Image: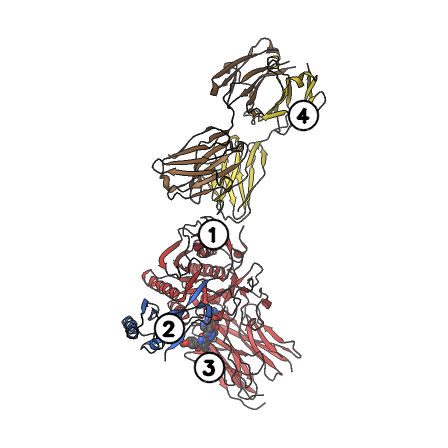
Amino acid sequence: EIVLTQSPATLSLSPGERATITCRASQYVGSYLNWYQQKPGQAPRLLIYDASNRATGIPARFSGSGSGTDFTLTISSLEPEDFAVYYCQVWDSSPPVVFGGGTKVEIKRTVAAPSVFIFPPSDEQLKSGTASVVCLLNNFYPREAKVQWKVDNALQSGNSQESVTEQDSKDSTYSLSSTLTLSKADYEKHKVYACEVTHQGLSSPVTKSF
Amino acid sequence: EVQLLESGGGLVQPGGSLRLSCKASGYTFSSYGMYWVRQAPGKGLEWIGWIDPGSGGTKYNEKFKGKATISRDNSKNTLYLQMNSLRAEDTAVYYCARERYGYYFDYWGQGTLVTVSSASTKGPSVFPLAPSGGTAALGCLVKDYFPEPVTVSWNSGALTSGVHTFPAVLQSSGLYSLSSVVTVPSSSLGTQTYICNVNHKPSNTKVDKKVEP
Amino acid sequence: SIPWNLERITPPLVEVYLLDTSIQSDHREIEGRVMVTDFENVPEEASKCDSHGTHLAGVVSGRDAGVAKGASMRSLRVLNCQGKGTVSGTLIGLEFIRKSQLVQPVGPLVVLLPLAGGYSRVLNAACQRLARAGVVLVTAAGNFRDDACLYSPASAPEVITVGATNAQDQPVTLGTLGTNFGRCVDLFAPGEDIIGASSDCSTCFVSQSGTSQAAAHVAGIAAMMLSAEPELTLAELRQRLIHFSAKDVINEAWFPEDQRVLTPNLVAALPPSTGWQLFCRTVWSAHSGPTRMATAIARCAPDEELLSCSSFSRSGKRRGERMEAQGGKLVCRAHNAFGGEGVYAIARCCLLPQANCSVHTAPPAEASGTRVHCHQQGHVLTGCSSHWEVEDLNQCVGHREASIHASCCHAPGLECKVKEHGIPAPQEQVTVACEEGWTLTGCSALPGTSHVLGAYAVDNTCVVRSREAVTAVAICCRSRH
Amino acid sequence: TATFHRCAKDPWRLPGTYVVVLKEETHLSQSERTARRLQAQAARRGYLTKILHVFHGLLPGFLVKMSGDLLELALKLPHVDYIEEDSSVFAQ
Ligand SMILES: COc1ccc(-n2nc(-c3cn(CCOc4cc5c(cc4Oc4ccc(C(=O)O)c(F)c4)[C@@](C)(CC(=O)Nc4nccs4)NCC5)nn3)cc(C)c2=O)cc1
């Protein structure tokens, strides 16, 4: 079977800057390769068909090239709406279709540090019998970060969950919210709690003791 | 115009089966190939099967060999999908896509979400996240609800700047937990009253909670 | 990028007829350009049924991986789902072409025959009748690692027989088999690991190997030649294929020893294009066999002129050769000696219009030896031949006990000269080649020599096979402009 | 004076089907008459023969499906140049 290998997995660029995405076929596919654009909450959209032809109603900044095994997709000037997920597609015998892994085009801006905030379990939640410690990491860049929960200088055993917002519409930043969920009995027989943040510049633990 | 109207999304019990439809309009239904392609959140495109509305000829992905079945009704210009013995990994957004034979996928469905869970409908418990320099942030925790989604607004929608409502997380109980935070100047903490407006539409649960240190 | 088999293809109303299996005309590589005729004649009777012809249609006119990108093709079904056919069913397909030639308007017709059976008298006769009607027939040599003269339509003198070469320009090997060879083969072409249209899906590609892929490659070149010059005759087209081919790139060690001299060392190419120049080619006769009065006869193709005649024997027991007029053309006749294994007659076939070559013979003189020259106005000496009746012994010279023969061609536009090279104690062969821009017309060995097996031309090099200095004598001609 | 031809590669021979090739100047009416004369002489001897095709444009003659026993009889027919036994061709 044919395998479509896309490179890179993530492309971080600035608007106006040029973008090049590569799709490599494991076999000869001629010029019968397609490109798709997928915006979040949407279905993919045909971008380039037959490796070089622009689909109807797509701007001229999108251009495709290649024949055989190596294929490229070029965006001359990055418009802010061009930051999406890109897929290369080809037909095959068995299976009848092959999709690439996808390439996420990301907005690049200056390195921003997270405005790290900590939140203790609310007293109304303490009556319910389960504690939840929340660590906020507001408006940072890039999306790569790490949170290590420190209950009285011990580690994060795996009783924590986190979620990251999508890149902001205004400042192109990211935000994270980690939740250390502990039982009421384990929350009582401990004193100090902290969340250690790994981002650019220095380590920044933020603590709170009841 | 060409439209592909999907239907049959919702909740499926583990071991149960999803039953989806794809209503086609604006073209000669039998002259184009049709696929069912799914996509798990954050992951890529996974094809399920193919059908030729003319012949009835089908092709299936080997992973869903015994579990998947694709049929059609040319009189209704409708495509059908059935996927038996579902597991939590089968939770994805399912699409129906038109195949222009030998060229590309020219038309797609809107995307239908199917969630595999044995949990029952439950309203959330809303807990505040009290604040404590120049700018301070505060929020409220929306915990233990099923199914997703929940909508959070601040001060009945008058507070939009600096708001970050986070995606929910599926926890061990099978329930969802979410948090929404706003960043405000520390000076207006005493003057301005901050409330989060939680709405869990599947259970008609509307909760307003005040944030105070 | 561009597949290896298309490296020697320079891109600058012609119909290509295909007699093969069923084809998938809907394939993106060939759709809209390849027509499916209503012809079908197969013995002993889905995606596997189409596999062979689809690939070959893609090899000829494929949009991405074809030789003649966008060439008009018309397919006939003579091979079943297992790629098997009959000679009878093949004749009916050929008659269908002859009927289609008369209905449809005039234009160059290329008939691609990527099939082979044993030698067939009726099939070769059918190929002759079509070639007499102006059809260019391109055939596969066969994948039996055998002499292609034993296979039809490969053995038909009027067709272009194509052998197969790999990416390293070496003859294709497939287990105990591989490409055919011999004097019936015109040239070789890429025939291993050839990417082309797969009948599995409308945009699928598959790699296939064989003389069928090599013959389809040559049909592609021929269609491109006929698109640019639709008035090229078959003789002109055969000469151009030979002239455009890569030379001496095949290691002949792959071929059996007795087939190395017979097999042309040519791999098809289409170099960048560019007045009148002299084009010559070498033809080998059939082996004469053991008889003191046995005779090997080499003749040229219609529209060609015979300019020289040479002979060869692996044992050396021979009585030379002679040129004689049969019809309105000269023929190369080689003579065997008593107790000889047999001889080969070697002719030099050139495109020299209205040359009216005549043979001029001087009888043995038994004096100090024999001599003859071209004395006519606007005549040039193109070849020197010599034969003798004895069992043991601008001018042509021979032994005093032998007759001398001169080929005198009326060609005012040519200027000819003689190049010699002699070796006292030769190590099996003596070589002399024409300079750049010169065309070899005649290859002979100088008489009075110890023991010569024979002489033959290999492109523009005179090769004299050895057991006084043994001298290789080359007659080189070229146009004055 | 008529000759017989067959495949030298014995596994590729297809006896029972023959191509009766006539002399070059033979008219189509003479080809159809020869095929009728062949069918008549074979039926008088208890043999069933089938004329599969009659060649017009390319070469004079016809395609016959008959027993090999009739070859001596068919070679004695007038206007006949040669008869060739059908054989197999293969994709290369
Ligand atoms: C009426 O019943 C007949 C009875 C006998 C004859 N013949 N037949 C032959 C004869 C037949 N073969 C087997 C096929 O021998 C070749 C096949 C191919 C090729 C070259 C071949 O080599 C020959 C062919 C013809 C003659 C030639 O003398 O006509 C020759 F000297 C050498 C080439 C390389 C193409 C080629 O160059 N094409 C030619 N076309 C005419 C002259 S070269 N490729 C396709 C395939 N070898 N010799 C010789 C004589 C003297 C003769 O009277 C004809 C009809």
Q: What is the crowding at mark 3: few (fewer than 14 residues within 10 Å), some, or many (at least 20)?
A: some
Vertical arrangement, residue A150 with respect to residue D60, above or below: above
Camera sees residue C352 = no
Is residue C123 toward the left or the right of residue B199 in the image?
left
- Measure the C-alpha gap from mark 2 to mark 3: 43 Å
Q: Which chain is blue?
A: D
Q: What residue do we see at 37% from left, 61% from top?
A: C41
- Give the percent coordinates (x, y) of residue A163: 59, 26
Q: Quadrant of residue D19?
A: bottom left
Chain A: drawing colour: yellow
User: How far is the residue under mark 3 from the one under mark 1?
Assistant: 53 Å
| Disc on res. C198 | 1
Chain identifier, red in the render: C
Report the disc number at residue D68: 2
Which of these two is toward me, C66 or D10? Answer: D10
Of the numbered discs in the image, which one, if any, rests on residue A85?
none
List x then y, in percent, for residue C85.
42, 63
- Secondary structure at numbered mark 2: helix
Q: Are marks 3 and 1 in contact (CB under 8 Å)?
A: no
Chain B's colour?
brown
